[PDB]
Image: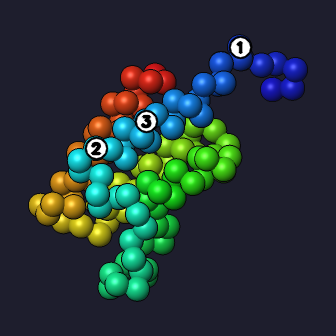
Amino acid sequence: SMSVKKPKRDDSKDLALCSMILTEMETHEDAWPFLLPVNLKLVPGYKKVIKKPMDFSTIREKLSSGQYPNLETFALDVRLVFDNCETFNEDDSDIGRAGHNMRKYFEKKWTDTFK
């Protein structure tokens, strides 16, 4: 509350560390469904169904231009990529499996880096 603060966590390396995680996601072999925005002219249903499209390139641009206020807003966008994937894709498809794998991969790096 006012004039009553928890001890200051060092957040000065967050930007760099989120960048590294993102690089690791970008370079994973199962990243391909997620590297670029889904082409809303060519994929029927996507525009109407997925209210908030998100992809790694878009996260990368946001990160690089100071549009994440903190590491939670970064993790929200990453998770949105996988949540969107689950909404549109059957679990038993290549893309559906890619999404499960990438989420698992992300969540481990996130825990190991920050928790």
Q: Is residue 11 left or right of residue 81?
A: right
What is the crowding at mark 1: few (fewer than 14 residues within 10 Å), some, or many (at least 20)? few
**Which residue shows up at 51% across the image and 37% down it?**
19
Q: Say which residue label 3 marks.
A: 21
Q: Is residue 4 left or right of residue 77?
A: right
The amino acid beneath tag 1 is Pro
Nearer mark to the viewer, of 2 and 1: 2
The amino acid beneath tag 3 is Ile
In the image shown, does 104 or 35 lie closer to the viewer? 35
CA gap, disc 2 and disc 3: 11 Å
CA gap, disc 2 and disc 1: 36 Å
Labels 2 and 3: the sequence-earlier one: 3
What is the crowding at mark 3: few (fewer than 14 residues within 10 Å), some, or many (at least 20)? some
Q: Say which residue label 2 marks.
A: 28
The amino acid beneath tag 2 is His
Residue 58, how many percent across, how many down?
51, 58
Residue 18, how many percent across, how many down?
51, 36
Residue 54, how many percent across, how many down?
46, 61
The kind of secondary structure element at disc 1 is loop
Please count the marks in the image: 3
Labels 2 and 1: the sequence-earlier one: 1
**Which residue shows up at 14% across the image and 63% down it?**
93
Q: Say which residue label 1 marks.
A: 7
**Which residue shows up at 42% across the image and 49% down it?**
79
Answer yes or no: is residue 80 visible: no
What is the crowding at mark 2: few (fewer than 14 residues within 10 Å), some, or many (at least 20)? few
